[PDB]
């Protein structure tokens, strides 16, 4: 107290990083739920399953990089419960994509608030960390999900019988 | 009488294995019938044909492993007629998949009854044999057929003109 | 009705091909029975087992080529029960070989009657099919079985203790 | 309702599998917490960190295989909150190892109760699943942790200055 | 007391595993005795020698896997004298094969009793261990020895001068 | 009677070789016991385990070469019970090493007495056999064990917490 490594690292930043870790672990859990929805016998869209499983594992990576940052800067990781997702039954490929898009925008908003806090606290290391590893990743993710939602809507998902099947095999395959 | 190899092998188990051999050979014949239905000039779904031909050959493997078990344990194989399948004309890709699912559940029920008999007779070798080579294979097969039935139903098979054609080329291809 | 592919294909030929399919599947089953007789603990002639298992699989090939022919010509496959073999206990390597020789001659006679029918119906495609894929195969098979029976008889099978053992390891190995 | 795949799968088993999924995800989170404790600047045992991170990822694998089983059998995954671990500060390499050993024994007890339930419900597929993928894994894990605890105790951890350092570099390296 | 690893492991099971270790070491010694009988100048059947030496080494493997199990589960290995085999002079290749068959059936009976005890004590780990590594190995071994005894009897062993010589060179070579 | 191969081979030598075979098999069993002591969860010195397991297998080799010698010279192998080791709990790495050193010196004394007997009986083949394959092996083994005991004593085994751990990983690893 303080850590021999700690320098220019505000307690508010440390707390906000702990909250961000929880949010990234939550996002991982949401995607894991979606992945296994798509492998149900009455859904059986294996490339939607693979896509969301990959997203789940990326969110765990996002959480771990923040945990590493906490240690690097001499903060102390404080974990909290990972809340269950809002749904187990995700309804359709389109609905899951729309929910993922909303999730990603929510996580983006949290990251932008974290960047504003880091700026306020004169922490350019933390600002750069977020810019380098988080903000463009989020923009790319949101854009990709937007593209997917548009194609599924235009194709007639979820009610048009061929739409999710064909998107599964040609876009996500 | 008895075989110099026979040990802890109840006559009821020996008889039940003979009945299971017949059922696996019957399942092989059903799938062979389906395979050649799909190669008719007025059906011509070559990947449905290939899929069911593969399933036919797997069922022969299942029969042979039970025949080998009978010899290994010192029982005597007693073959019976292999009954013809219930249909020659299987109507559609969806109908064949639904019939295959029912067949697999029926074969599964027979295997579960065989496991219950082996348990009752204190035959852990036979229990393990069924668990190792049959029960999970059946669960996997039933799940795969369930997945296929769901996709074909959602796509609008059998009446939607593109459904079986597209499933043939993208899932079974 | 008729199939858009059907041409110069008599209903009698179509029916005779269905009967031939059943006979080839029956021959496969006979050989499968023999194969597993030779793997009994009280018989244990592993190369006799392998030899008859191979013959079993070849007969399934013979059945499938006729099933393909039926579809190619626009006929409709009509499957029937596959009758069990005449024996489960095949007595000896010599007896099995003698039974196989009789089976092959019986199947040959059926093929010759099928060729006579095809000739009568002016079906040169069917005549050529039988000549190309069946008649010489049968002559080769009958000759091979004749050779095997002669050697086993001369060697003193089944009662001479070394005969089947030595034939198993030097001719069939 | 029910799933077209469901067979011999009791609702109690389905519920117990959902509880087991939560427990495996909890174990993953415990190990993740431990991994990042060991990377603190005031702990800095990088091979303890790597060891627990690996264990964390294995527990996620354990959770996923149960999620797959639920879908395979036609049950429905029902996720719950993942509770935070009991500690963020794990005190020492020895204490973390002792906590991991207790966790593994607790998870083992849950698996044994699940196997007893599956047995009671006559579900040999579920029994075999647990035996094949879970029970021996748990015994191996408990034994390994026991070995590690013994060596650390004998070496004088946590107070002997060289003990955890040397164990980190020679056993876990 | 108890071992920090021990869980769901009954003292009766621990004792029965110690007895099984002794029996497997005894079986190894029997086979070692047989191997060196066949290398006598007045026996000189080098492939019978090699066959039994291999079986001896496999039995040591069986003993070691049980010793490892004892440690894995937190039991304590308690070794006893390894009794000498019943004979040094094994009389003939046929007699040795018949003695080996009886030995294997006796060891199998002991394993089945061990499985019944494990079942009674609700130890699915131990049941699976026996099923996975012991019970099918025993069935395979008994069947192989049955096959060998049958061929040697039919060939006229031990009195027919060529029988053991030819079996040595063609089956065991 | 006598063996057609026997020449210059005294009955006393034949008997002494049988006693030596038993002693080498006993030494193998002692080392096997030690190997599995070191794999206990409350000992867990895996390189001590590996070292003694290797020594166990070498002693079996020593026994087999004497069994081969007996046959080569036309003597008859006479096996006896293999007595259990003096301990199951070997107390420590140092104590096991000290017990192994005493065992090796005892086996050496027996070999020297065997050489004296062979000399007395004018058997230069047996003298050379012992010199070539046994006497220098024993001197090397005794020296190696002496080296190990010295290092463990100097390092402070068994009570110094780091000693056996460090010797396990740097000398025996
Ligand atoms: Cl600071
Ligand atoms: Cl809350
Ligand atoms: Cl700044
Ligand atoms: Cl897209
Ligand atoms: Cl559509
Ligand atoms: Cl029996
Ligand atoms: Cl009937
Ligand atoms: Cl049982
Ligand atoms: Cl599908
Ligand atoms: Cl359509
Ligand atoms: Cl398409
Ligand atoms: Cl026509
Ligand atoms: Cl009839
Ligand atoms: Cl013509
Ligand atoms: Cl021939
Ligand atoms: Cl003869
Ligand atoms: Cl059910
Ligand atoms: Cl709660
Ligand atoms: Cl059950
Ligand atoms: Cl360790
Ligand atoms: Cl220290
Ligand atoms: Cl216990
Ligand atoms: Cl006694
Ligand atoms: Cl149990
Ligand atoms: Cl044999
Ligand atoms: Cl002879
Ligand atoms: Cl020969
Ligand atoms: Cl002499
Ligand atoms: Cl005594
Ligand atoms: Cl001399
Ligand atoms: Cl040394
Ligand atoms: Cl020390
Ligand atoms: Fe939050
Ligand atoms: Fe992504
Ligand atoms: Fe990625
Ligand atoms: Fe993220
Ligand atoms: Fe909640
Ligand atoms: Fe994200
Ligand atoms: Fe930048
Ligand atoms: Fe992303
Ligand atoms: Fe039946
Ligand atoms: Fe399949
Ligand atoms: Fe396959
Ligand atoms: Fe099957
Ligand atoms: Fe019928
Ligand atoms: Fe099947
Ligand atoms: Fe079981
Ligand atoms: Fe299958
Ligand atoms: Fe017929
Ligand atoms: Fe052939
Ligand atoms: Fe062939
Ligand atoms: Fe044929
Ligand atoms: Fe009949
Ligand atoms: Fe034929
Ligand atoms: Fe021709
Ligand atoms: Fe042929
Ligand atoms: Fe729980
Ligand atoms: Fe692990
Ligand atoms: Fe691993
Ligand atoms: Fe786990
Ligand atoms: Fe809480
Ligand atoms: Fe675990
Ligand atoms: Fe199993
Ligand atoms: Fe583990
Ligand atoms: Fe015993
Ligand atoms: Fe073997
Ligand atoms: Fe082997
Ligand atoms: Fe054994
Ligand atoms: Fe005795
Ligand atoms: Fe054995
Ligand atoms: Fe064996
Ligand atoms: Fe002695
Ligand atoms: Fe050595
Ligand atoms: Fe060596
Ligand atoms: Fe030795
Ligand atoms: Fe004693
Ligand atoms: Fe030695
Ligand atoms: Fe020399
Ligand atoms: Fe040595
Ligand atoms: Fe070192
Ligand atoms: Mg300082
Ligand atoms: Mg603070
Ligand atoms: Mg998938
Ligand atoms: Mg007998
Ligand atoms: Mg009977
Ligand atoms: Mg085709
Ligand atoms: Mg037309
Ligand atoms: Mg007609
Ligand atoms: Mg075979
Ligand atoms: Mg339905
Ligand atoms: Mg329910
Ligand atoms: Mg690290
Ligand atoms: Mg304790
Ligand atoms: Mg006790
Ligand atoms: Mg040899
Ligand atoms: Mg003479
Ligand atoms: Mg004498
Ligand atoms: Mg080891």
Image: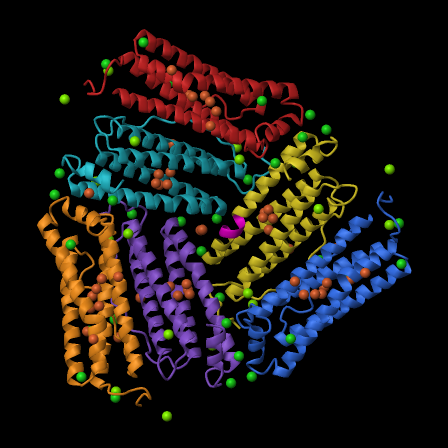
Chain colours: A red, B yellow, C blue, D cyan, E purple, F orange
Image position of A103 with respect to D122: above or below: above
> Is F30 in front, or is E118?
F30
The residue most toward the top is A120
Q: Is residue D3 visible?
A: yes
Image position of C46 with respect to A96: above or below: below
Name the spot of residue A148 as percent of width and height, x first.
57, 21
Quadrant assignment, res D94: top left
Quadrant assignment, res D151: top left
Magenta: predominant secondary structure element? helix
User: Measuring 23% from the left and 47% from the top, which residue is drawn there?
Assistant: E2
User: Measuring 40% from the left and 43% from the top, which residue is drawn there?
Assistant: D134
Q: Is residue A156 visible?
A: no
- What number of labels is visible? 0
| Quadrant holding the N terminus of chain F | bottom left
> Is D172 in front, or is D134?
D172
> Is D52 in front, or is F42?
D52
> Is F29 in front, or is E73?
F29
Residues in magenta? B131-135
Residue F89: say if magenta: no
User: Measuring 25% from the left and 72% from the top, which residue is drawn there?
Assistant: F81
């Amino acid at each position: 107290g303080p850590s021999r490594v700690r320098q220019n690292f505000h307690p508010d930043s440390e707390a906000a990083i702990n909250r961000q870790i929880n949010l990234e672990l939550y996002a991982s859990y949401v995607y894991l739920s979606m992945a296994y929805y798509f492998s149900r016998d009455d859904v059986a869209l294996n490339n939607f399953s693979r896509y969301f499983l990959h997203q789940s594992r990326e969110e765990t990576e996002h959480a771990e990089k923040l945990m590493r940052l906490q240690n690097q800067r001499g903060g102390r990781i404080r974990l909290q419960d990972i809340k269950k997702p809002e749904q187990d039954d995700w309804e359709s490929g389109l609905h899951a994509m729309e929910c993922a898009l909303l999730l990603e925008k929510n996580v983006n908003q949290s990251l932008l608030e974290l960047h504003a806090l880091a700026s306020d606290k004169g922490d350019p290391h933390l600002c750069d960390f977020l810019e380098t590893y988080y903000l463009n990743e989020q923009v790319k993710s949101i854009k990709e999900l937007g593209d997917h939602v548009h194609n599924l809507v235009k194709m007639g998902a979820p009610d048009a019988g061929l739409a999710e099947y064909l998107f599964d095999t040609h876009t996500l395959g």
